[PDB]
Image (tube, rainbow, N blue to C red; front, side, top):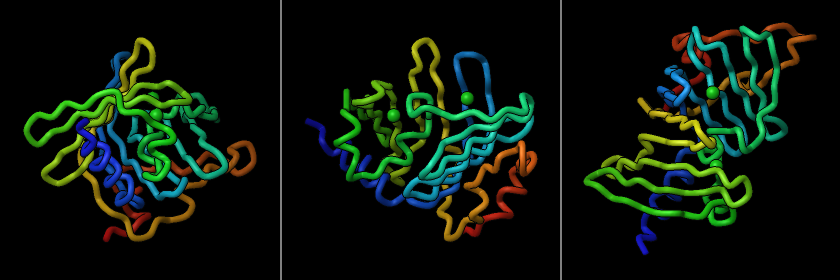
Length: 190
Ligand SMILES: [Cl-]
Ligand SMILES: [Cl-]
């Protein structure tokens, strides 16, 4: 078995603890959106879609929530409806949580098909072997495929803590809306 794929995949999970990613997201429903994804393992992440895509997703150890500016709505995201679940996975937990369905290797790219043992959600991961980075992530939700393209990955040395907070808008008001430049102003690169 091409077990090296898990090794490479595991390596990424161990070394990408604190990153910011410029990404493009495409779906079967026609949406195309760009955004900034901040990951601060063990549990914290912020998916900051750029305008006009009115959604911010903030995940912490206690909660994973979504805010829709257009709907003025706060929601909670089930692990089965979290497309960023693999990126938070600890390597030690990989074998407990995922099973590799298949591996395909072409030139510098390696495509790994995996499935979550609990949520049974299938996903496809593209690995760039030259720089050992994830380039494409595909999530299969019944009749919809969500594709996340990793346009740029940078390591972060310190995050503004409030980037991983989503305060009750009913009490503390609407969360700050951040553009690409605005969000880059609130964390320090390595
Ligand atoms: Cl998953
Ligand atoms: Cl979405």
